[PDB]
Amino acid sequence: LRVRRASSWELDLILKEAEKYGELLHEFFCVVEGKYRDVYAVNEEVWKIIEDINMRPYSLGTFVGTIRVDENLVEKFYPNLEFFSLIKLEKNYVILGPKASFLFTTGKDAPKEAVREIKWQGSKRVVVLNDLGDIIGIGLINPKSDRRFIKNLKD
Amino acid sequence: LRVRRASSWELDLILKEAEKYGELLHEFFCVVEGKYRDVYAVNEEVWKIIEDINMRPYSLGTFVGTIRVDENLVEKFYPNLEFFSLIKLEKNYVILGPKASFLFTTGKDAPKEAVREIKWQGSKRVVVLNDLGDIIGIGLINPKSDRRFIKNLKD
Amino acid sequence: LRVRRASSWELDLILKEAEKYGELLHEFFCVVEGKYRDVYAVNEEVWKIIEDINMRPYSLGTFVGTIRVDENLVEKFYPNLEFFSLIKLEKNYVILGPKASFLFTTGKDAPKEAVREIKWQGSKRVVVLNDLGDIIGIGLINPKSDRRFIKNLKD
Amino acid sequence: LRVRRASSWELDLILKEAEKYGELLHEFFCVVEGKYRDVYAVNEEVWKIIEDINMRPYSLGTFVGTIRVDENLVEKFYPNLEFFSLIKLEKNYVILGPKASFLFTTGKDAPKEAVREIKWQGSKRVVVLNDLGDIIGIGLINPKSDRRFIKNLKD
Image (cartoon, rainbow over all chains, first blue to last red):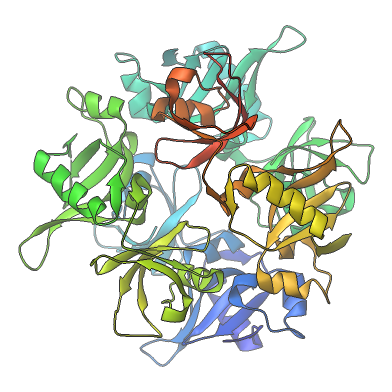
């Protein structure tokens, strides 16, 4: 592993992803060149340090996902759920009732009737909130389906 | 311990507290009559059940604080930090920078220069947010002080 | 959906799994008959209640995995990581150094040189501990390989 | 603020405390000279770095407590609960039943009848485990009392 600050390109990929949902509140990222490019949210100090000193991933901050080239030969940032804690959430989310929220955390899809609020602006992937506004996972909207309207991806 | 649904009075005390900060998103509470009255956020089903069946505190839901009579012989709800996860936060909070946020979680007060945003409407106790908008504790505003502008109460 | 206490057979499937690793410390389980049989660790009181009163999964306790029929037409309990918190761990585990432990939590396999201790007794799946003895995930031992000796399954 | 590796003396104060309970599994600590000396468990890499580069507390690792001079003018390390995650626990602990464990996490003392196991070797402060062997807090043994045999200190 080489560990470095994120490239301008990589930041844009990370930003593109965050901006599907809202405002990216966190500025500083490092990349761990492994098999794939792992993205860490780092504090400003670590971001500064990493210029002069290689640091191991366990000293960096928070792993928030990976950059890979997808099927279409398009580089994408693939966030983990932790990445979403960096976002002031504004859109492409659904709020589920408490029962459905709970079930969602067990890997269950959510039915449409369980959706209390949806603010959807296009994204396939939506942030799934429980009824307390907390992120419980990421879901795949299934615009046509009812029982499985929000397909469980991550929880 | 008798375990019961919260009284209308007790709900009002709980609501009074939540409404210093925003909208109480959670409706159902039980009270565990111990030495003091412990408040649990319970789901609707448990709230319904508790009518017919005593349940032990470990089956109820989330302990969110205690009702006691304060110094002025005034009954107050004393929330724990968990109570605040029930509130759509709107006011009486401060947002700290990441460095100060971190230190706050170690029990440190926050200086005024660390305050990135304050939406204060009167309360002595403010919700302290980190720079990601997450609740890191409760603070006592010290309107006149600088180094200890937000006194650490809970984190 | 039907929620009931776990059958004798289901308890054996659960116990079989726990006993690969150690002593199952938790006695009481319920099953939620959904698409698949989901297993909840419940407290004794809930286990008692669920006799006379249906409860919803969000009132039950802790989701710990699912019973399904595998490829061999053999019923198996598939634990999630939370299940392992119910086990006094004794065997089929590895302990990783801190660097490898951290990386494991990011979905990385662990190399053999990272294994500080292994107490392996046959199981494909091993509990992966960090250097503090805390469960960080489950891994697939690849006895013959070096770079990917512990294949990451869950973390 | 000055951030440095822990002194030999400070390491002894930390080790003294850990060794009341078992084996300190973590070797590397830094100290943040604030109002008091705050102790951070840091990884080896950070411990190495902190030689040549000041880092802020938010980059260090895990805050585990504070060194202060007590009433007897004796320097002591005061751990927080997180410190105990660094210890292979061997002694000065009690194990509580699940009901009492839960109540303990709400700040309640534990009665003697709730103690399932006690391995006590002298310490006023005992690690309190739940019935799954997980640390739920620290308690003050009140050898002579029954209702409040384990006084709740931290949970």
